[PDB]
Amino acid sequence: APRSYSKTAKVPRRPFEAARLDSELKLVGEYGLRNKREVWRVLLTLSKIRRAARQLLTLDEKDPKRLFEGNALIRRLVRVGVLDESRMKLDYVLALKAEDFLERRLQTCVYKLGLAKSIHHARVLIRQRHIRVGKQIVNVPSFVVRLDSQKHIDFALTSPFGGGRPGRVRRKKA
RNA sequence: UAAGGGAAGUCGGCAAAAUAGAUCCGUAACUUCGGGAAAAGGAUUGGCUCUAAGGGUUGG
RNA sequence: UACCUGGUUGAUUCUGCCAGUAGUCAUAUGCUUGUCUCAAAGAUUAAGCCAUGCAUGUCUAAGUUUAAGCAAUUAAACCGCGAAACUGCGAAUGGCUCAUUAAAUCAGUUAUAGUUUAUUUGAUAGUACCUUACUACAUGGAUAACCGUGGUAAUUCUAGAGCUAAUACAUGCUAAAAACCCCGACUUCAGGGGUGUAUUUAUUAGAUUAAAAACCAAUGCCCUUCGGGGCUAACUGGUGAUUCAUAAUAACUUCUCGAAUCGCAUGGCCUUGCGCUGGCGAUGGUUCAUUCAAAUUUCUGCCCUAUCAACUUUCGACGGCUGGGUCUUGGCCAGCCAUGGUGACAACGGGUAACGGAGGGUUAGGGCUCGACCCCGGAGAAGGAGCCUGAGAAACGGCUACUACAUCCAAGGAAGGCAGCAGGCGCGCAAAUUACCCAAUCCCGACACGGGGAGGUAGUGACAAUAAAUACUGAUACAGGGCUCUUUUGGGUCUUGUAAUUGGAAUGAGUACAAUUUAAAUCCCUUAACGAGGAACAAUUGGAGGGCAAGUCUGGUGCCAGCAGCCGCGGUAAUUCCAGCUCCAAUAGCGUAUAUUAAAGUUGUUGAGGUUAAAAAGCUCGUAGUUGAACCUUGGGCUCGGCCCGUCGGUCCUGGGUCGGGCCUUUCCUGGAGAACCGCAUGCCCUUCACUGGGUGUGUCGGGGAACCAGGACUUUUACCGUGAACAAAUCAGAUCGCUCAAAGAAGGCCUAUGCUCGAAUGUACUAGCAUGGAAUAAUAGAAUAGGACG
RNA sequence: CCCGUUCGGCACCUUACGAUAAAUCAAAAUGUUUGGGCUCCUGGGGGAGUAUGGUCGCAAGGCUGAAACUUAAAGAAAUUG
RNA sequence: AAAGCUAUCCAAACUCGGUCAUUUAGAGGAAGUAAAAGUCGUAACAAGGUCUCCGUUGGUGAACCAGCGGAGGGAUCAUU
RNA sequence: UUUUUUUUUUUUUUUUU
Ligand SMILES: [Mg+2]
Ligand SMILES: [Mg+2]
Ligand SMILES: [Mg+2]
Ligand SMILES: [Mg+2]
Ligand SMILES: [Mg+2]
Ligand SMILES: [Mg+2]
Ligand SMILES: [Mg+2]
Ligand SMILES: [Mg+2]
Ligand SMILES: [Mg+2]
Ligand SMILES: [Mg+2]
Ligand SMILES: [Mg+2]
Ligand SMILES: [Mg+2]
Ligand SMILES: [Mg+2]
Ligand SMILES: [Mg+2]
Ligand SMILES: [Mg+2]
Ligand SMILES: [Mg+2]
Ligand SMILES: [Mg+2]
Ligand SMILES: [Mg+2]
Ligand SMILES: [Mg+2]
Ligand SMILES: [Mg+2]
Ligand SMILES: [Mg+2]
Ligand SMILES: [Mg+2]
Ligand SMILES: [Mg+2]
Ligand SMILES: [Mg+2]
Ligand SMILES: [Mg+2]
Ligand SMILES: [Mg+2]
Ligand SMILES: [Mg+2]
Ligand SMILES: [Mg+2]
Ligand SMILES: [Mg+2]
Ligand SMILES: [Mg+2]
């Protein structure tokens, strides 16, 4: 069977716009990202919700299609944490910005919760198996943490921090 | 009249051979549009027994 | 997310193209390449040629066993396993490719009342019918396997000779009794023959439209208070529609089927006879229905081309009739007759580097383009044709013949079809191992057991896609931005950088005990002891004048070499070449070439342009086509209801607007099964003008207007719009679930457990077809020689 | 011959509520606020109205009518020299 | 009941012509395009020194010239 | 209103309060 697969980013329409290049570099440095692709990734996803939210606003308020689809969109937004309970219904979705979707990343939250003291150290720890969510170890910095899950981040029980067992370097100096 | 070859004969296919009636089919370049044209090239053809069509005259 | 920029000029506004830009599930190629998940992959050209190996076989108690086979069995009488062979079934599935093919395939929608059907499923068959020497307590003859004798160089070649089985082949009796038609000696009224199903022919039934009196022609029958009455009966299926379903009669047949088959359990009865009976199954069998289907078939819809305008018809072209052939209809074919059929609304012919579609890419809307290829349909197996077996084939891992190619040879002969899976050659810009296995998905077989290059697994694999390493950090010294002061003792220690100055912790790339995965392995996942200080475990691809982010740097060359998609650079001061340094863009990726899309309002229906930039025929007539003046029921009123816009909030009723319904204003019957109006049997209020305690479903007088069934009559017809039914999955949009997130997938979650549960949604069917409503808009008819309407 | 009205013509003069890139236009207006009806033609410049096929003509020629290849401009109206 | 045989039918294949479609060789001839410091003239752009252009015909090394008819895209929007 | 032909290739400009 032909297995479905898709793309998570788009190359910008104009390759060498000075304003666009500078704005992207603001997000890369602030959040300690890797390249421009995962910046384009978040913008593509953010466009998807914004495109979907706008197309429903064109319908009728009483129209059942808008009611079901609109509430479905908000539930993911509220659950993820980019949106609050007081943001009804969809006019506040259009105010979402690329920055807002970026704090919900595990790289940012591990830093905003004081686990790491620099955003570059924060990403390194996650990818290096030193951060777990609940009972689950997560090593993907793009892991989007929900508000419910935001209260269950701590170091891994196998890591020298939290677990206590010395690592390879500390054992070597013995 | 001649086996096999088929112009190697000869200045040269000279001489001979080959084709040939009728019916049906098919017919090129070129053209002064009239022709070429029977172009080229094919098929049938006997005997016997039948069948059908194609007329006239006189009385409606 | 409805978008532009550079380039004609000394400068300007345009027409207009070129270039730049981005996407592609779109191919190739260059450089580079650490990890995880998923994964395309000899289509383009040569449907070209193929060495070799494999890809289709199959046994249950339940078809046939004397293996001189095993295993325990009895002298014997034959079974527990089980080979060979006969028998049955399958081999017509699957897999591969896209050569042919343009009303053809195909798609949606129709029909088979014009047909066949192995298998599955449910039913389903009583027949004195007539042949053998006869039998039903049971018929006959062959042939394998086997023993032995060979042939040829050679084949999955076979002969001669001796046996021997059937669920292989061929025969063959039947069940009583009822009822019906025919023949019938017998004074005016016994007996014998035939009657299952299958086939063919012929005939009959298979009904039903409102009622009554006369010579009957024919017996009129019964009831006869001997007038007169009833009566040759009662019942009778289905479809919109049939000569249908079905029944009956007269016959017919190279006379089908109606069990001479196998296993388990073995039990009952009395006339004790090796007597009569008893289930479950297996296989098989006629008809009907059903299933998988197949085959034709109705309507509508296909790219370019007029430098294709007429095509078909001698020898079928359009049709009618009779017959043949077919499973069946049909010019499908054979005979006879007639002259038709298609076309400017594009027939016929030609091209396709054309299999059709679901769909892929890209788009605000309208579109453009691709679709060999994981799914459905079609066709093919080197190129044509023919055919056997078979339910099913015009089969090719079947046969026969011809052409091409090709193999062995003792030269007499024999044998062949990779567009099946690997592999090779050739071809090309262009595409992988002559690996492992049926464990998973399913299929086939006599079948729980065997087989499956279908299929899965692994290897090659920068097709494409997802996640994501190449580093983290403290202090010291310095600088900057602040803060109270400017006595500038300024770092004093809030922050950020430079720290070429140092100390630290952590880990995976790799590696490997062990565990895990798997048919067995690999990898991922898990994890002992290993594995990091730059020299290491070292990221690349393009560029730095503009479009377009980034150099006023240095050396070399000197219109040379060279660069440059375009404009342009280079002639001894090159921001463009060759290099060093520095920087910019993307980053495990980047560049290049070709195809296509947007940009392109540069194909314009939406939506281009035609005085001068390309473009109004020299002018007029005119056919096809396209388009075409106005005009026919409007207005008003009576109302009734839904929804929306306000205050009333009943628990923790109100006006207006819109929409719809019936009536007035010149505006369907038959039987009504229930409806109903006119009064209702009761009932209801009322002028003081008849008292009351009853009765749901209703009968009749009667029924202007109505949904109900079912028969018929009267409806102008098309276009258009609304609604409804039906309308493969997959794809797309889209709902849910922490595969560690993601691409994905259809999972999962809860309880400690005992086992408990939600899901696996929803939308999408343009055009053509079906049903109904709407009656403006666009067409067409109607009464004029009235051959007009009305009882 | 004079004055005026009207229909139908050949044109002209001023103006822009409009149009066009502009020159200019009572049509080249009523068009991004884009749909009255019909026909024909054009898609950067060349090659080229050429080659070939067809057809008409006595001929000269007419009508129909490409492609390979090549090129970053060709061209229109105005401006200052 | 095998071989064989009679007559139709389906019909491969080959030969011989015809037609369509698509490629391809060719002496020679006549064009186009491109490349530049080649020879000869100077036809056009000003009244380009004979105003330019169109159709047709004839001629000439070459651009071109001339006759007939037309146009202004003219060097005249005008003479009472 | 006598006539007056020709001129070898390339080279001829940028930013803001
Ligand atoms: Mg001689
Ligand atoms: Mg557009
Ligand atoms: Mg120009
Ligand atoms: Mg310039
Ligand atoms: Mg382009
Ligand atoms: Mg198949
Ligand atoms: Mg049955
Ligand atoms: Mg006929
Ligand atoms: Mg017939
Ligand atoms: Mg093809
Ligand atoms: Mg092909
Ligand atoms: Mg055959
Ligand atoms: Mg192969
Ligand atoms: Mg550079
Ligand atoms: Mg640039
Ligand atoms: Mg810039
Ligand atoms: Mg245009
Ligand atoms: Mg011109
Ligand atoms: Mg012009
Ligand atoms: Mg004119
Ligand atoms: Mg009309
Ligand atoms: Mg006039
Ligand atoms: Mg164009
Ligand atoms: Mg052109
Ligand atoms: Mg000019
Ligand atoms: Mg002049
Ligand atoms: Mg001029
Ligand atoms: Mg000069
Ligand atoms: Mg000169
Ligand atoms: Mg000169």
Image (cartoon, coloured by chain):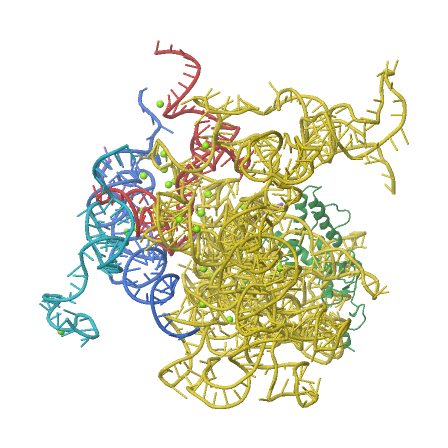
Chain colours: A green, B cyan, C yellow, D red, E blue, F purple
Can residue A104 be seen in this snapshot? yes
Residue C94 found in image quarter: bottom right
Depicted C700 relative to depicted C107: above or below:
above
Depicted C375 relative to depicted D62: above or below:
below
Residue C282 pos. (x, y %): 65, 69
Can residue A32 be seen in this snapshot? no
User: Tag count in the figure?
Assistant: 0
Residue C666 found in image quarter: top right
Q: Residue at x 75, y 45 (%)?
A: A88
Q: Residue at x 77, y 76 (%)?
A: A171
Depicted C661 relative to depicted C289: above or below:
above
Depicted C390 relative to depicted C697: above or below:
below
Q: Is residue C724 left or right of residue D31?
A: right
Residue C81 found in image quarter: bottom right
Residue C492 pos. (x, y %): 80, 60
Report the front residue among A9 and C612. Answer: A9
Report the front residue among C381 and A60. Answer: C381
Report the front residue among C635 and D12. Answer: C635
Image quadrant holding the C terminus of chain A, namely bottom right
Report the front residue among C387 and C320. Answer: C320
Residue C623 pos. (x, y %): 38, 35
Residue C90 pos. (x, y %): 56, 68
Image quadrant holding the N terminus of chain A, namely bottom right
